[PDB]
Image (cartoon, rainbow, N blue to C red):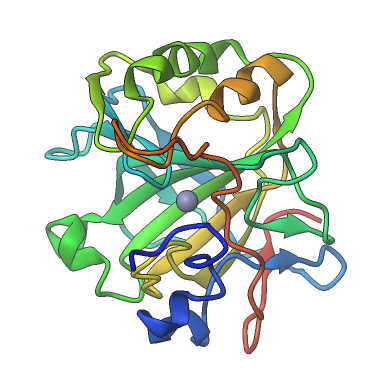
């Protein structure tokens, strides 16, 4: 059967269809802050989202993706541990059924309520499909969400979820500015990893921001109203769509701050 986050098709079963699940550079991982190495050679991140053009929001059956026009670099990520230009193609979240879980990466074993993933691909490879086949093909910016004060810039996303409740549903979602989802500081940890959902390709340079953003209980509650199922099928609430931490193995996590 198709992979998912249930008891019979969850993360522990993925290796049967995707052997790379037991690979050498799988994600997510636990970030041990005392073992992370401060690297003074790491450059500051350069986030240019002023010309971003959002197009649509889609319920993929595993999460909801906000898609962007990536036919030109209008929204790009550069600098940091990256060499070259990476174009933003989509962002999505992972969340839990309770505020005490939901994030994929953890910090000193601490789990956050959710995790935002801004996915970018290396322009030198021409298209997203080619990029995922390369070790330096993608750059994913990870941002933790803690429950507290509401995040104004996230509300437009929250209000449209009713229209894409079930798998396969999509809605026009134009003029959304992703800058409203970024924390004040851009200090980060970085390590070589993989996509956290099948095909689990090891083509990602992970950039995880140290500063979480705050969202209200009401905002996260609305995420939990989505469905894994398609319309007309038995209702399965979309919650706990996160993969647990994987072995770090032969990898070093570097920090841009000390
Ligand atoms: Zn993700």
In the image, residue 1 above or below residue 105: below
Q: On the image, which quarter does residue 172 sit in? A: top left
Asked whether residue 66 is in view, the answer is yes
User: Where's residue 2, x and y in %?
Assistant: 33, 64
User: Where's residue 32, x and y in %?
Assistant: 81, 67
Q: Is residue 100 left or right of residue 48?
A: right
Q: Residue at x 41, y 84 (%)?
A: 16
Q: Quadrant of the N terminus?
A: bottom left
Asked whether residue 216 is in view, the answer is no
Q: Residue furthest right?
A: 34
Q: Is residue 56 left or right of residue 97?
A: left
In the image, residue 149 above or below residue 117: above
User: Where's residue 209, x and y in %?
Assistant: 64, 46
Q: Residue at x 38, y 25 (%)?
A: 165
Q: On the image, which quarter does residue 131 sit in? A: bottom left
Q: Residue at x 65, y 42 (%)?
A: 96
């Amino acid at each position: 059967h198709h992979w998912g986050y249930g008891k019979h098709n969850g993360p522990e079963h993925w290796h049967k269809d995707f052997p790379i699940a037991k690979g050498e550079r799988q994600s997510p991982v636990d970030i041990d802050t005392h073992t992370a190495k401060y690297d003074p050679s790491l450059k500051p991140l350069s986030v240019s989202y002023d010309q971003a053009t959002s197009l649509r929001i889609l319920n993929t059956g595993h999460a909801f993706n906000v898609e962007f026009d990536d036919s030109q670099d209008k929204a790009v990520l550069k600098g940091g541990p990256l060499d070259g230009t990476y174009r933003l193609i989509q962002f999505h979240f992972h969340w839990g059924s309770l505020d005490g879980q939901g994030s994929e990466h953890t910090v000193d074993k601490k789990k956050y309520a959710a995790e935002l993933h801004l996915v970018h691909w290396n322009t030198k490879y021409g298209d997203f499909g080619k990029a995922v086949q390369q070790p330096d093909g993608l750059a994913v910016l990870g941002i933790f969400l803690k429950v507290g004060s509401a995040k104004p810039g996230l509300q437009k996303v929250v209000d449209v979820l009713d229209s894409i409740k079930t798998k396969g549903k999509s809605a026009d979602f134009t003029n959304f500015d992703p800058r409203g989802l970024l924390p004040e500081s851009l200090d980060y940890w970085t390590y070589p990893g993989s996509l956290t959902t099948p095909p689990l390709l090891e083509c990602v340079t992970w950039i995880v921001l140290k500063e979480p953003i705050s969202v209200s209980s009401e905002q996260v509650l609305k995420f939990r109203k989505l469905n894994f199922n398609g319309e007309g099928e038995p209702e399965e609430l979309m919650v706990d769509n996160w993969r647990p931490a994987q072995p770090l193995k032969n990898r070093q996590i570097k920090a841009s701050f000390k």
